Structures are given as C-alpha cells and as structure tokens.
Image (cartoon, coloured by chain):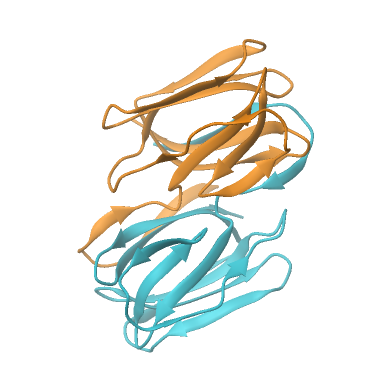
Chain colours: A cyan, B orange
Amino acid sequence: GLTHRKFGGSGGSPFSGLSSIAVRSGSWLDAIIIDGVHHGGSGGNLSPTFTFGSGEYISNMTIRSGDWIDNISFETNMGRRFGPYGGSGGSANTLSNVKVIQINGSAGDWLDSLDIYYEQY
Amino acid sequence: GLTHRKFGGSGGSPFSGLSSIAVRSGSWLDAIIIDGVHHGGSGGNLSPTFTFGSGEYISNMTIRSGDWIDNISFETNMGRRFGPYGGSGGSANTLSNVKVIQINGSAGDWLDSLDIYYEQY
C-alpha cells in the first residue's frame, strides 16, 4: 500500500515536487494548474499562482465537491492562504493539521476528481 | 500518518502533479527538475526531460545513494525508461512493482536526499 522511503543523506533545504498551484474556475473548477502544468479545460477565469516557499506546505485545505470539484482553498503552515475559487455546489470537506504531499486527480473538459496524498498529524 | 483521500466524481483522464522529470548530473546528481522546477545546483549536464503520459507512472526505480544522491533511473508502467544519470558511488536501492506518487527531497548546491512516496503493489 501507500508508503514512503528516504534515500541519501543529511543536508540542504527541503523541497517538494508540489511547487505551485493555480486554477481555472467559474461556478466550479475547470482546471487545476500544478507547477504550471495544466489539468482540465479552457473554461472559467485563471487564478493567480501560489508558489510554496522551501519548508512551506499545505496544512489545511477545503475541497467542495459532489460529482465534480466545486471549490478549493488552502492555508499553509506559514499562514498564507489560496482561494477560495469556484462556487457553492456540492459539499465542503476539510483536511486539517496535515502536510499535503501530492495532488493527483482526473480531468477532461473540467476537473472531475482530486486524489490528495498527505500526512495526517 | 501517510494517507490519501479522493474527492469528486467519476469522469475524465487521470493526471498526476508529478508530470515530468529531468536531472543535472555528472559523477552525482546536481539537481532534479520536477515539472520544470529546478531543485539543486548549477553543476553537471542537463538530461532530456521525461514527460509522463496520462495513466503513465513510475513502476520501477533505482536510486543510487550514500550521503547524497549518486544516480537515478526509472521505468514506467508503459515500458519507457529514463536514465541512468549520475555515477557509481554509493549503493543501489530499487523500488519495484510500485506506482510513484510524489518525489520530494532536500537540495542545496546539489541533490542531498529524495523522499519517494509511492504505492507498493
């Protein structure tokens, strides 16, 4: 099942492959843009890009969803916030006191689902 | 601890926030470049970029390491290969029959450690 392994030694500053997030949104999420890579369709309006600093990660996140993704927001361990973007359909679900490791998902003409991998503290 | 949750509904094509990989390497790994975002120093030579197709993910991976990262290669579930890049110090460790979810790590003037998060089948 889901696991992790470290390789290598002590030094340096932390980084994550989850380096920046933006979305396209209207009433719902048309796309999520991860590290500048577009996932979803061309609809809605493009949000600003949120870029994580070294050692900064998502610690609280709310995803509103039903059959598809309606809304997203998150806060980092340094107190910064992204969103909300999207609308008010579906129901809110919240991850709190976490460290988000990755955001995978499925998308076509819009953003259908998100797979969040995270440490729960 | 480490976990995952899905939000949303059925449709669309799979995607991952781990979308492409390149490295800078010489005798060792000077940098890893994830989704075009540079992690590490300016030394060595830049490899080509490997870009995952939808539904394509790392299924086997070898990381050679000691105090730092010496070498990396991987194969995908579609049979494509990246690397090896780097040199022959340290010792080889292999993840096999997996699905890599994320590559985090620590880097400074070069690539010091990698945190691989993955499903073990």
Q: Nearer the viewer, residue A46 or B113?
A: A46
Residue B41 is left or right of residue A43, and the answer is: right
Residue at 58%, 76% (x, y): give it.
Answer: A82
Q: Quadrant of the N terminus of chain A?
A: top left
Q: Quadrant of the C terminus of chain A?
A: bottom right
Residue positioned most to the left:
B11
Image coords of residue B106 (percent x, y): 70, 39
Image coords of residue A76 (percent x, y): 65, 67
Q: As displayed, is residue B48 above or below residue A103?
A: above
Q: As displayed, is residue B64 above or below residue A28?
A: above
Looking at the rendering, which quadrant does residue B33 occupy?
top right
Q: As displayed, is residue B46 above or below residue B52?
A: above
Residue A48 is at least partly visible in this image? yes
Looking at the rendering, which quadrant does residue A8 occupy?
top right
Residue A94 is at least partly visible in this image? no
Residue A91 is left or right of residue B25, and the answer is: left
Image coords of residue A44 (percent x, y): 36, 84
Residue A104 is left or right of residue B13, and the answer is: right
Residue at 73%, 33% (x, y): give it.
Answer: B110
Looking at the rendering, which quadrant does residue B32 occupy?
top right
Instruction: Please count the marks in the image.
Output: 0
Q: Nearer the viewer, residue A11 or A39?
A: A39
Image coords of residue B2 (percent x, y): 52, 46
Residue at 40%, 63% (x, y): give it.
Answer: A38
Q: As displayed, is residue B21 above or below residue B26?
A: below
